[PDB]
Image (cartoon, helix red, strand yellow):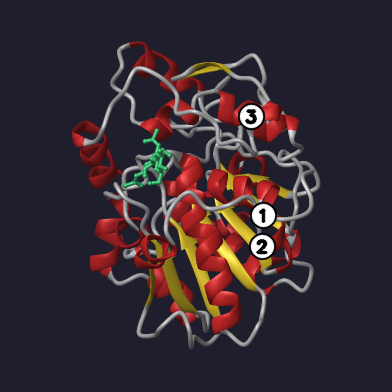
Amino acid sequence: LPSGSDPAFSQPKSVLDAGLTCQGASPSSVSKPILLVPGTGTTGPQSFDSNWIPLSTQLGYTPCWISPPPFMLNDTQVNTEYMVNAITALYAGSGNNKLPVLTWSQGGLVAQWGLTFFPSIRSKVDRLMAFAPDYKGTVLAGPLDALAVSAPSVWQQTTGSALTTALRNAGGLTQIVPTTNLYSATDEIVQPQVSNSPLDSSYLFNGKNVQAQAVCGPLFVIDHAGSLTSQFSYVVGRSALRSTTGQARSADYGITDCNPLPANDLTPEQKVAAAALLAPAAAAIVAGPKQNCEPDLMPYARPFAVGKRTCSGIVTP
Ligand SMILES: *[C@@H]1O[C@H](CO)[C@@H](O[C@@H]2O[C@H](CO)[C@@H](O)[C@H](O)[C@H]2NC(C)=O)[C@H](O)[C@H]1NC(C)=O
């Protein structure tokens, strides 16, 4: 795993600062913050307004989020800078206290990419609660890449990409901070997710990998968005956030919790929105940038994906 000093940011600090926002507070003076890293094709609010923003508030946290432009569709390496900058700011803004990081979809990949290549944040992140993370990308994006209808981050989240290869070879497939991965075998966006073993895209060695079906049975069905908004997910997430170990405890949830519908504590209005979470994301992807090649890896990541091909050609150290 990489060690030492953090790589330089490619973006100006003021640009990175503009992507961070906290509910009812400034990042420089926030109490018990929680960083929410959104999914592909959405902004912080679009990913969490109907779920984890109000739910984390009810848990005693001040929700904060990053909204990398445009809609998390650009280079994942850049989206991560927003997160690293956010952590640095929220940590100092909370009296130098570690803070939890909750994520959805691509947001998990960004968190892990950050913990792997940016050593400084490893002592600033308390725990990681990842919902439907795609550390190994997804095989379902291959076809889209071939037609060149994929955004920069879709190329990178494709199984076999230079980005996912660089993460694996750098040792990013092992948890770096206490991590809880809640996913579903019936995820229509991320695959493979059916083996309930290291082959799954949301699996991290030494982490609390929770495949919903392994707990609720083969008849339990929650999709990509469901992995984030379901009552089952709220219970597992609450467990992860409260745990003294930093990971979700099996003793905190059981079959009773196997409710595929949105979290009970959500207002009926928030429930309807949470059920249609994927709608805005699909819209953003249809209207967003599209290209015919995977974005070039930044210098700090090239040594780990030699031989792979990106927009400029073959990768060399
Ligand atoms: C989207 O990602 C690209 C690729 O990382 C960013 O472009 C780079 O930006 C830096 C800083 O401005 C430049 O020094 C590089 O030359 C750019 N590279 C390329 C290939 O364009 C871009 O800034 C990001 N845009 C947004 C809105 O996040």
What residue does disc 1 label?
Answer: 6
Residue at left 43%, top 53%? 11
What residue does disc 3 label?
Answer: 302
- Mark 1 residue element: loop
Q: Amino acid at mark 3?
A: Arg
| Tag 1 near tag 2, CB within 8 Å | yes
Q: Is residue 295 left or right of residue 116?
A: left
Residue at left 32%, top 50%? 69
Q: Quadrant of ligand 1?
A: top left
Query: Would you place residue 44 above or below residue 159 in this image?
Result: below
Relative to the observer, which residue lies in front, 61 or 216? 61
What residue does disc 2 label?
Answer: 121
> What distance separates the C-alpha of mark 3 from that of mark 1?
15 Å
> What distance separates the C-alpha of mark 2 from that of mark 3?
21 Å
Task: Give the x, y percent position of residue 192.
Answer: 58, 25
Residue 227 can be seen, yes or no: no
Relative to the observer, which residue lies in front, 169 or 284? 169
